[PDB]
Amino acid sequence: RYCKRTIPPGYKVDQVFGPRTKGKEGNFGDDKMNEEGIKDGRVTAMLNLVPSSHACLFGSRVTPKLQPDGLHLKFEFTTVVPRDDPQFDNYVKICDQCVDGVGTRPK
Amino acid sequence: RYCKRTIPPGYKVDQVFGPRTKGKEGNFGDDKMNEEGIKDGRVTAMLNLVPSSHACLFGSRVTPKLQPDGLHLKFEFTTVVPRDDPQFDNYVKICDQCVDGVGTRPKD
C-alpha cells in the first residue's frame, strides 16, 4: 500500500511521496529535504514526532469517507511539543523551514 | 513521547491512548476493541491502513500551530482503499463498528 512506503537511501522524497506542495498533502519538506531524503539530518528529528502505528490508529481523530472510488480513511494526529521541551526550538525551526517549504533551501 | 506509545499485551486501549470518544481524537474503537486491545483481530486488520512513519511525514498534510503551551503539530493522512479492493468490505465494516463506536459492541 502507498501508506506503507518508506524512502530508501538515494531516493528523493518526491520519487516516493509526490511533488512537495503547499497547504495540501505532501507539503512537508523544502528543496534540500526533497533532494537528500532520509539523509537530511532534519528528517531523523522530525520522525520522533510522527505517531507510531498504534498512536496513529488510537490517538488520532479518524474520519472514514466513502466515495465512488473507495474508502478515504483520514487520520488526524496531533503531536504536542511543550514550550519548555529541550527540543522545542529545533522542531519549530525545522517546521519553519520545511512546511510548505517547496521552492526554498535553508540556512 | 505520547506519539511513540504502543499497546502492550493485556492492556486496554484507554490505558494508553485515553477513552474512546466521538468526533474527537481517540474516536477509533468500540467497547470490545477498547477492552481487548491488540488481542482484537480487527486491530490487526486496521494497522494495514495506518501510514508508515515516512508516509506519515511526507504523505500527510502537516500543519504546525503554536500556542502558549507549545507546538501542536497536526498530521492529516488519508489512506485510500479502492472499492474493488478485496479487503474493502472488511475495512468498511470495521470502521462502521469502531469509528465513534464507544458504547457499543459488535454482534456475535
Image (spheres, coloured by chain):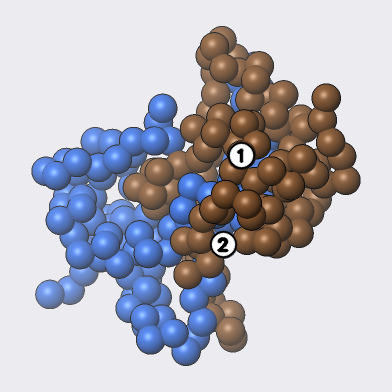
Chain colours: A brown, B blue
Q: Residue at horizontal 14%, vertical 44%?
A: B9
Which residue ends up furthest to the front in the rendered image?
Answer: A10
Q: Position of residue A41 (x, y in %)?
A: 62, 31
Q: Residue at horizontal 59%, vertical 43%?
A: A38
Q: Position of residue B66 (x, y in %)?
A: 68, 25
Looking at this view, is A30 or B101 the one in front?
Answer: A30
Q: Which mark is residue A78?
A: none
Residue B81 shows in the view: yes
Q: Amino acid at mark 2?
A: Thr
Secondary structure, mark 1, is helix
Looking at this view, is A101 or A83 the one in front?
Answer: A101
**Is A32 placed left or right of A57 in the picture?**
right
Question: Would you call the spot at circle 1 few (<14 residues within 10 Å), some (14-19), or many (20 or more)?
Answer: some
Residue under numbered circle 1: A39
Cβ atoms at labels 1 and 2 below 8 Å apart: no
Identify the image quadrant of the C terminus of chain A.
top right
Which residue ends up furthest to the bottom in the rendered image?
Answer: B84
Give me the C-alpha separation between circle 1 and circle 2: 26 Å
Query: Which mark's residue is nearer the viewer, 1 or 2?
Result: 1
Chain label for disc 2: B
**Is A52 placed left or right of B70 in the picture?**
left
Question: Would you call the spot at circle 2 few (<14 residues within 10 Å), some (14-19), or many (20 or more)?
Answer: many
| Picture layout, residue B88 above or below residue B2 | below
Q: Position of residue A71 (x, y in %)?
A: 51, 75
Residue under numbered circle 2: B78
Q: Position of residue B5 (x, y in %)?
A: 34, 36
Secondary structure, mark 2, is strand
